[PDB]
Amino acid sequence: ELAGWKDNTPQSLQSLKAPVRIVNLWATWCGPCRKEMPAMSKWYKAQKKGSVDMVGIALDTSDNIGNFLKQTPVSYPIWRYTGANSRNFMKTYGNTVGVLPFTVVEAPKCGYRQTITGEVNEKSLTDAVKLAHSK
Image 1: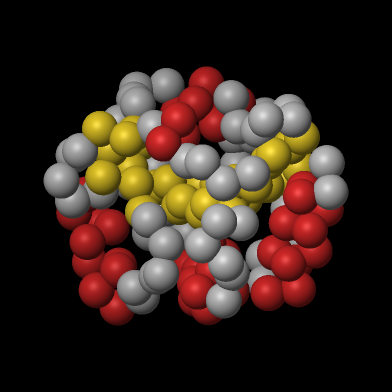
Image 2 (image 1 turned 120 degrees about the vertical axis):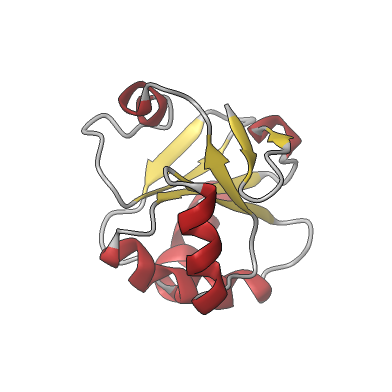
């Protein structure tokens, strides 16, 4: 239940191959999400090709995302949720309260999953990822 934000091109977590995976759930009316994104963007460009995948999955409209990336473009893939039960969708990522923003780091081949509590920034991402690699 994921597609490219523009193309509506079907997508899935199954396409992500790195040992560590970072999923950010967000939306364009989220001021906190919007604050964190340029930091995630800059962090991401300085990671090695093989080491991590990052996606920002928008619980928002193709229209609203388009406008946002116009002003705040990021270095990582942006997809869009296409389903009807948003609460249930977030739950599968460990987001039980159903709140945004929400960023979670995983090493899927190992089942390891940890939400990033506190500000998502360069030091936060680096530490979380290093912890996940170690699993």
